[PDB]
Image (spheres, rainbow, N blue to C red):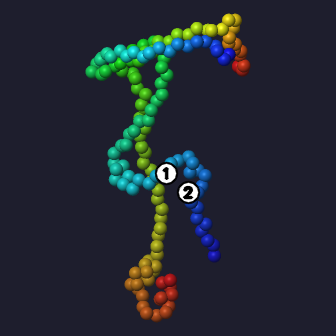
Amino acid sequence: CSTLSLVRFLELGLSVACVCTKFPELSYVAEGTIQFEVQQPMIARDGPHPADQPVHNYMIKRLDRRSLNAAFSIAVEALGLISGENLDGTHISSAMRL
Amino acid sequence: EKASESYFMGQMQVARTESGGGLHLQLTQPRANVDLGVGFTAAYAAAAL
């Protein structure tokens, strides 16, 4: 036979790049935007800064949604024995079930 | 050099002025310097291109 050597993500190296945190209700709250800006530094230049509008140093960052998929097909003769529907008391059918 | 120049830092003042429904006050802090070194006290030179 052959085993399936599993691999953990946290035990890899790439994990340094991203902070992973589980957010259970996200798919519900993902109907709207989250929309948090971050910052922007600014030097103190000499000379008086005009009394105008352009004082912005808070560019906005918006969330993007991503997913993952998989396929896990199961045969028809399997769930028959699994649910005990197509089963009888013989030793044979209690072996195929295993 | 170690003591290139004196540097006097004053106190801060504000300018409380409202303009266009928004409070706009600026900060100011007067400064002053003097190079307390007889003869030259700082030299530079072009390193790369």
Tag of residue A20? 1
Q: Can residue A49 be seen by looking at this rendering?
A: no
- Judged from this view, the residue extending furthest toward the top is B39
Identify which amino acid the numbered label 1 is placed on: Cys
Residue furthest bottom as drawn: A90
Q: Quadrant of the N terminus of chain A?
A: bottom right
Give me the residue at 56% from left, 10% from top.
B33
Q: Secondary structure at mark 2?
A: loop
Q: Are marks 2 and 1 on the same chain?
A: yes
Q: Are marks 2 and 1 in contact (CB under 8 Å)?
A: yes
Quadrant position of residue B23: top left
In which image quadrant can residue A22 be found?
Answer: bottom left
Q: Nearer the viewer, residue A80 or B28?
A: B28
Image height of B1 relative to A80, above or below = above
Residue A36: x percent and y percent? 39, 39
> Relative to the observer, which residue lies in front, A32 or A50?
A50
Q: How many marks?
A: 2
Q: Amino acid at mark 2?
A: Phe
Residue A9, picture quadrant? bottom right
Closest to the observer, A64 or A43: A43
Residue A9's mark? 2
Q: Is residue A9 left or right of residue B49?
A: left
Residue A61 pos. (x, y %): 43, 38
Say which label, 2 or 1, has the lower sequence index.
2
Q: What residue is at 61 percent from the left and 66 percent from the top?
A: A5
Q: Which sits in the foreground, B36 or A59?
A: B36
Query: Disc 1: which chain?
Result: A
In space, the residues marked 2 and 1 are separated at their CA atoms by 10 Å
